[PDB]
Image: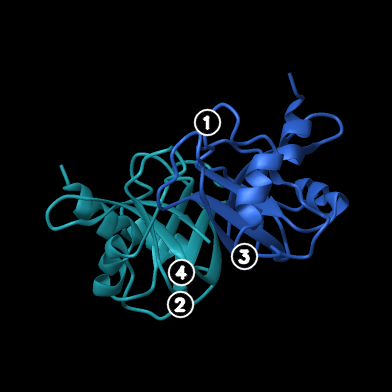
Chain colours: A cyan, B blue
Amino acid sequence: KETAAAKFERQHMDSSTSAASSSNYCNQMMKSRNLTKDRCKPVNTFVHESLADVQAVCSQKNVACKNGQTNCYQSYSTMSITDCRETGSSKYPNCAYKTTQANKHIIVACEGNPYVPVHFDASV
Amino acid sequence: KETAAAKFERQHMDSSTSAASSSNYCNQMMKSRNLTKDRCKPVNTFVHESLADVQAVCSQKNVACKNGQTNCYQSYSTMSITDCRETGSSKYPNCAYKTTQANKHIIVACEGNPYVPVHFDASV
């Protein structure tokens, strides 16, 4: 099993590019990050900033999570992100994703020592 | 009880302004839309476009909802929105919200005849 922090990294971190490279970015990334193995993960966001910058969000603006939890944090600045969502004729095991690039604040839930992101809540 | 469509309108529609008017916008709106009555609703987004334009999203890009439902739709264009989230020392019944204005695509779940929005899923 993964640690919660490692799972966040696998699902949400892509510091290797400044933004989605093509309309096929999500198709490629959802597959290579193992998010299409057991099923098509319906929605997933990748963040194109350094791991350090994303971890730093845990020391930024404390805000509520969508579910009412109090350990969520909103980035003070906008970040380059890519939203991936199942679209068209996506059907497991033939998953298909829409790639939407944007620059927005991220909201993450943080836990542990060190206090690091363990869930991607939303972007604004 | 409200219809699902009416509840969406009450929670998410604000066509009366082109964007949040002040840092107090969310405090005012969460109260006046009855989202602080039984508890502080932790997170809520208002859309500053016409009702017609928001309803029209149900005929736009079919995408998966976060929970795996297949009746979500993403707006082709960005829309003026305001994200409201509990912050600081928000504690029922003294709710307190952060106001974040943005221009993003909206994703809504649609149902019924007429086919109209019944849930706000996310913004991109």
Q: Are marks 4 and 1 in contact (CB under 8 Å)?
A: no
Of pointers 3 and 1, the one earlier in the residue sequence: 1
Given residues A27 and A5, the one toward you in this image is A5
Quadrant of the drawing holding the N terminus of chain B:
top right
Residue A123 x/y as whole percent: 49, 59
Which residue is disc 2 drawn over?
A: A19
Identified by mark 1, the residue type is: Arg
Residue A21 x/y as whole percent: 47, 78
The reply to whether label 2 and label 1 mark residues of one chain is: no
Which residue is disc 3 drawn over?
A: B101
Q: CA distance from mark 4 to mark 2?
A: 7 Å
Compared to A91, does B2 lie above or below?
A: above
Label placed on residue B70: none
Find numbered disc 3 in the image and state the secondary structure of the residue it sits on: strand
Quick check: can you spot residue B33?
Answer: yes
Q: Residues within 10 Å of mark 2 (few under 14, many from 20)?
A: many
Q: Chain of mark 2?
A: A
B11 with respect to A71 (left or right):
right
B6 with respect to A8 (left or right):
right
Q: Residues within 10 Å of mark 4 (few under 14, many from 20)?
A: many
B106 with respect to B91 (left or right):
right
